[PDB]
View (cartoon, each protein chain N blue to C red):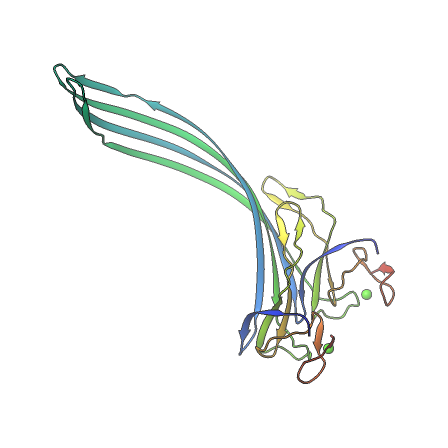
Amino acid sequence: PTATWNMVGCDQNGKVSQQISNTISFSSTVTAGVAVEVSSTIEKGVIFAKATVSVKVTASLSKAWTNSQSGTTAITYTCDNYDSDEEFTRGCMWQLAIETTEVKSGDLLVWNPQIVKCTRSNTAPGCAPFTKCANEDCTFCTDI
Amino acid sequence: PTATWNMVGCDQNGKVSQQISNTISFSSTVTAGVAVEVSSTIEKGVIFAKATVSVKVTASLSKAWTNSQSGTTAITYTCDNYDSDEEFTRGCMWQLAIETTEVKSGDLLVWNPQIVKCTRSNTAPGCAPFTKCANEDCTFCTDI
Ligand SMILES: [Ca+2]
Ligand SMILES: [Ca+2]
């Protein structure tokens, strides 16, 4: 047993499944505005102390145009059987620990592939992807 | 019985399931703008009180570019059976109380694993993950 796996969820009493999603989006906005300011002031100031009062009135009008596009991918995995080939009715879903080479398709679709495994209980597996316990206490692995 | 569980939902008359989701997202915006202000003022002021009126006209034009990416994981659990192996037609769903080591996969995928259990009724279980009542009043637990 070489590989190390991360546990992703355990259910003692039924199914476990997962969905993994990535979104990429690009957006842009164009804004055009105009403003009109009409102020005035009255200031009286002779022999020593000066005092003013101002009244300003502003009016604005803008218009923005946005457009955007996104793309998303979503992979879903379900636990259906153990390595022994019996139906899965409980316990844990595992994800291979190696980080992996991202897949792209054009500018806004991206995947990052996972390799998922399901086991009877929550004791961590060691066997390689597509490799099964060969002996009772799982110190050897054979091709599935 | 060692473990403590939190109740997450009870249905006296059918199924209970849950879905747990985590999203991580990074975004950035770049904004470039340009403004033109064309003001003027008329102020008349001799012997002793001064008075002005101002008219300002502004026009702006900006453009923002945003791009973002997110990633989300969603694990779903369903209650299918009791520890006795009968079909689940009512009862409660439980979540192990210990906080748990988060799994990551690159920059925007995160899980935090749960261990879920389902029971016949709403009396709190104490048995360890993958461990079942061994006796009528559940003071001892055996491997499932
Ligand atoms: Ca086989
Ligand atoms: Ca059993």
